[PDB]
Image (cartoon, rainbow, N blue to C red):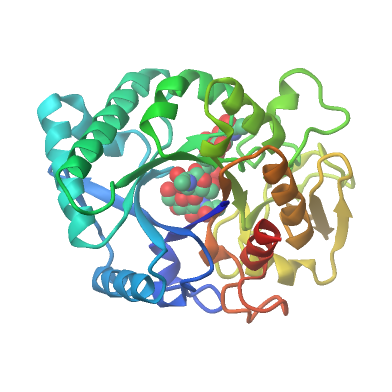
Length: 364
Ligand SMILES: CC(=O)N[C@@H]1[C@@H](O)[C@H](O[C@@H]2O[C@H](CO)[C@@H](O[C@@H]3O[C@H](CO)[C@@H](O[C@@H]4O[C@H](CO)[C@@H](O)[C@H](O)[C@H]4NC(C)=O)[C@H](O)[C@H]3NC(C)=O)[C@H](O)[C@H]2NC(C)=O)[C@@H](CO)O[C@H]1O
């Protein structure tokens, strides 16, 4: 059966409506797997820094009581944690063992079903440390299993969808044996970090008709194909789908993909971060905007004034699910359900319109 793996985040709790998210906003039957982002590491041991830590625990038990099949994982890593967050824990056998033992105890004590390691990114420098850490975790989880009456703790990893970073960071065949699945981060293909700075879509399914050479790697279709080619079984690929888009401020009258941009788009009023918008912000931006669907890339962008936003909607997600089924992938992953219109109060499409569309397509 296809998985629907849903990340939610610690920091959405600080937002104003309609972006104010706490774990009680989670629908227990919406996803097959939930992933909390992110735990940290202190004195080589896993810890959660979250004033709402006790709420998270209560909610975990409540959700799992309501849906005995639900799996809830703890993620550590992410972009801001970077590689530095894993040091000094990773630099010795004794310090990794301390971490791993703390993980098993913590996960069991708080009713989690497994660990997601989203190291952003190992790159060439930390390839070895990451490979070793994953291997030692898998082994320890297996050893824990043989001595327990409970199910084996799951181990997953959020991984790059960029060909160069994939080649640099990962020993893929080994990863295929140690991981239950990958959460393929198939988004951020384009954004305001690029040079030269031109518009491009966050998460195009396929390449543009004019894309040749390396430009042709920056899409979901290519990333999924590449991971499988490198030795990840298709059923262990859980394909990431974003509920946010990337915005640009246009530098000229041109409004097409590849148009000149002067910088990131204006910050949204709720997420307050120049360069992206959550879906509950996008649906407001679309009012008064001009929407274009790329027939080649299979996704929409919209323009209003000097703002250009590449994003995903119900339609582009239905196409992405047809793709994942056709490639026999393990399911879909969402970054992140707290940026869908979870309350339904913004987009006039009911609660969780994007994730519900995915769930529906997966089961139809
Ligand atoms: C083709 C290619 O290789 N492109 C590179 C880009 O991928 C890269 O941008 C970074 O991409 C990573 C995924 O590879 C992304 O991190 C994951 O994705 C989400 C959404 O972007 C991140 O969410 C952010 O988390 C931080 C805390 O860590 C929050 O502060 C922030 O608000 C979140 N943003 C959003 C929109 O929700 C996650 O951290 C992470 N997910 C997991 C499971 O780990 C980075 O965010 C991307 N970096 C930036 C600056 O956007 C790009 C820059 O490195 O380089 C290209 O080459």
